[PDB]
Image: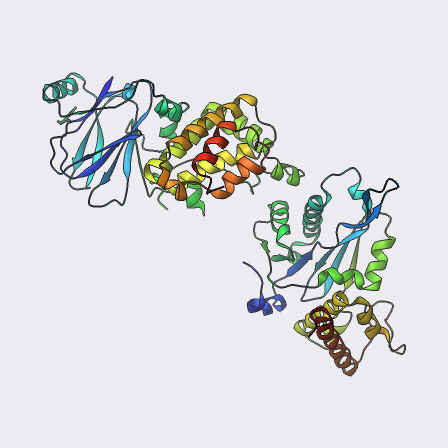
Length: 300
Length: 237
Ligand SMILES: O=c1[nH]ncc(N2CCOCC2)c1Cl
């Protein structure tokens, strides 16, 4: 179990750690977060009391270094930092913990939620979508745009998601115009899976990461990317059976975890109705269709 | 974006554009089978591709052999239209290719966009106008060449005959759409109006009769009366 300590908490802020969150008051004696499970990526995120605008936060993996958060009063945000030195990192943490003003990552033992939401997410792939190579962790916020959004303006602060566009020469073989547009199996399996992602695990990892950025930061281009990656699978007549089985599980836990009150902005009616009721895979997402119908029947 | 009453004069400016109409591509007769079920028999069709400024009509004849062994023909017909329009553009010299293609039915937008991906600079547009191009098969010489075709074939016409020698392309299009609207509302009356006087003939190289300026005013008036009438007969007014 790993620890992300805090130098201080000088401004009132709601702090998120994965799917959990807690309020910290201005200059409250808050020390950080302990007992973070090893083996998964994590995200620690922030919404200031005085400006609910700009949710922001950091993707990290404690196996890749020692990390702590301290507030920067010039840039006005909680910044993640690394201690390459270990003894001093353990040494600074040592005084802070007998005086236990440190919240415990509050995982229930039965609960596989985080694992189910991050099963295929890897830090190495996150760091290719979020380019800032001098750090081992990745900053995301509400307003970052995606490469594809910028094609339709600062590239260093972009989300370099894989570009999917159903009306593109990449998606459509000359001479198979109708065939490839109505059945995207070529684009999914040859172009994207064999060509760009290499395997379905990498594909699912980007899909899961896009969802999490949409949910935790309300990042709109991430939501577009999540729906695009779902629609490309649902609009393919030929999909490996193991990918469909796993997709249904992935989406089920995403829909389960989505705040009930955020469904109106985070879910695209057209895609979900198409995917569950019209697409080739309309009969292959049993768990996802069941939870969608019982939880958001209005959307459908 | 879309073409409507507000940007109507754009059709007659000097940017090459084409209207595409797919109504008559997939044409069937419905009939009973010996067992008393229903079946369709396809008949020859055509793509109606028209330059509204020049009157040049690119009439691509769709022979019924192109449906043999195919499924979901109404959906295929839209993609077949888009394939043939794309093939037409590629056949034209660069300086004759259109800068816009306006489709008369929105269901043509995606098929044509996908087929024209190689032409990112050609804008594909819908329209809100309710244009009467489905009545093109009421033009006797156009119907005749479609029905006689034994194979796929492109035939070139000027739908304005020689009108542009005397009138503008705005007026020529207004005349055309009035004639076609009349032919669509009441084909027989419309056709009687156009031919009642046997001293006015259709030149071998024309589609419509050789009316003087004055006779066109009379004719145009008769077509409006017809359209207003049928609008009464239909709604009782
Ligand atoms: O590694 C570190 N280096 N330097 C300061 C630091 N802090 C400051 C005190 O609060 C905890 C975080 C840590 Cl943990």
